[PDB]
Amino acid sequence: KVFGRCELAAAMKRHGLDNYRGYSLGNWVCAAKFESNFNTQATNRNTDGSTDYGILQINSRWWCNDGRTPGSRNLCNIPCSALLSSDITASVNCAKKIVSDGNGMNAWVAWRNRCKGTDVQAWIRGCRL
Ligand code: NA
């Protein structure tokens, strides 16, 4: 599923991401834009041989099982394929664990490089939430 911007903002807010670990809704929407372009089916291979899955490009190195990432963990206890669903529940549940791991949203290199310190409220502008 390719989410619309306000459509994803609503879904994230319903699933309690708005101000989760102190990160406002616009931070999450911004991260999703630059990680996946709001596409739940987005996959990208990393240089280390792990893969990033779904709207928030969650990494098989630590967070989900894809069966092809040697010496990797599955800390969200989910198949990485579950992170590609039209229903973002799994991605949001897993993202809550990631952002709690100690470095906040710096875990998402695209958030640090493209969203951090920017006017992230622009990403929820005009949305009925
Ligand atoms: Na894994």
Image (cartoon, rainbow, N blue to C red):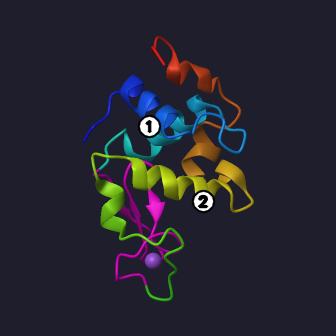
Q: Which residues are magenta?
A: 41-69
In front here: 124 or 50?
Answer: 124
Name the outermost residue toward the bottom: 71
Give the answer, above or below, for where 56 lies relative to 27. below
Res. 65 image quadrant: bottom left
In which quadrant of this rendering is ligand 1 seen?
bottom left
Q: In the image, 99: left or right of 110? A: right
Q: Position of residue 43 (x, y in %)?
A: 33, 59
Circle 1 crowding by C-alpha within 10 Å: few under 14, some 14–19, many from 20: many
Gap between marks 2 and 1, in whole Å? 20 Å
Q: Residue at x 51, y 58 (%)?
A: 94
Q: Which residue is mark 2?
A: 97
Q: Is mark 1 within 8 Å of ligand 1?
A: no
Q: Position of residue 6 (x, y in %)?
A: 41, 23
Circle 2 crowding by C-alpha within 10 Å: few under 14, some 14–19, many from 20: some
Could you tell which of marks 2 and 1 lies nearer the N-terminus?
1
Q: Residue at x 41, y 69 (%)?
A: 78
In front here: 125 or 100?
Answer: 100
Amino acid carrying mark 1 in the image:
Lys
Q: Position of residue 28 (x, y in %)?
A: 55, 38
Q: Residue at x 42, y 77 (%)?
A: 49
Q: Position of residue 88 (x, y in %)?
A: 38, 47
Q: Main secondary structure of the magenta part?
A: loop
Q: Secondary structure at mark 2?
A: helix
Q: Which residue is mark 1?
A: 33
Q: Which callout, 2 or 1, points to the residue nearer the camera?
A: 2
Amino acid carrying mark 2 in the image:
Lys
Q: Secondary structure at mark 1?
A: helix
